[PDB]
Length: 90
Image 1 (cartoon, rainbow, N blue to C red):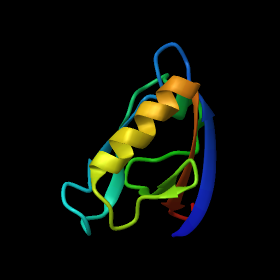
Image 2: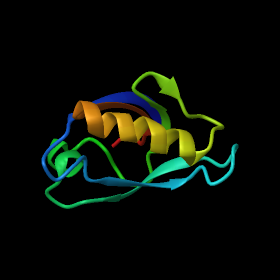
Image 3: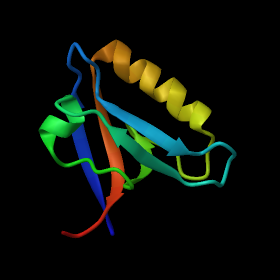
């Protein structure tokens, strides 16, 4: 894999992706379910299984999903997000 930045404008339906892991610090955080026809799906770049490493410049590596909860709460509020993910070369 390799690190990629993915900026998404929020839609009325949201960003359209779920998260897995980071249940405790040190447990890796991954992109889970991507909502069909949602913002992430339509953009096309984000994939389930991509490892999340930062949100809007804030590193989430080794951190709790609770930090991501906070970061995505703000991402909702501002109506956009910039995700750094490790992605599979296709």
